[PDB]
Amino acid sequence: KVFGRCELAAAMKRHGLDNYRGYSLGNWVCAAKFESNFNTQATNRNTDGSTDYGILQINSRWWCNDGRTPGSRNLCNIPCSALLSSDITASVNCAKKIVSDGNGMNAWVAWRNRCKGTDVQAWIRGCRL
Ligand SMILES: [Cl-]
Ligand SMILES: [Cl-]
Ligand SMILES: [Cl-]
Ligand SMILES: [Cl-]
Ligand SMILES: [Cl-]
Ligand SMILES: [Cl-]
Ligand SMILES: [Cl-]
Ligand code: NA
Image (cartoon, rainbow, N blue to C red; front, side, top):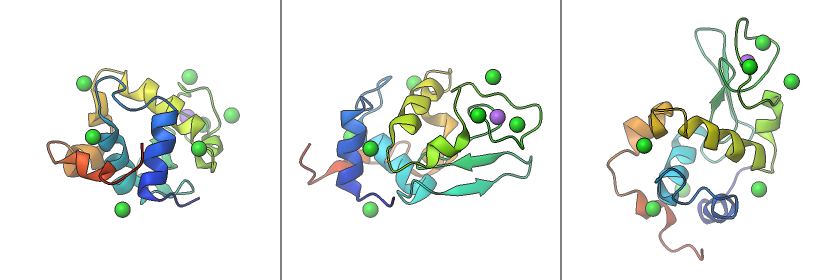
């Protein structure tokens, strides 16, 4: 599924991400825009052989099982395919674990390089929330 900006803001708000670990909803929408262009089916292979899955590009080295990342963990206890669903529940639930892990939203490279310290409120401007 390719979400609309406001549609995804609403979905993320409903799943408890607004101000989760102190990050406002615009941070999560910005991260999704630059990681996946709001496409739940996005995948990207890493040089190390791990793969990033779904709207928040969650990596198989730590967070999900794809059966082809040797020596990896599955800290979210999910198949990585669950992260590609039109239903963002599994992505959101795993993102809450990640953002709790110690480096906050710096875990997301696109967030650090393209969202951090910008006017992220612009990402939810005009949305009925
Ligand atoms: Cl947009
Ligand atoms: Cl915001
Ligand atoms: Cl594996
Ligand atoms: Cl594990
Ligand atoms: Cl699995
Ligand atoms: Cl959803
Ligand atoms: Cl933090
Ligand atoms: Na894994």
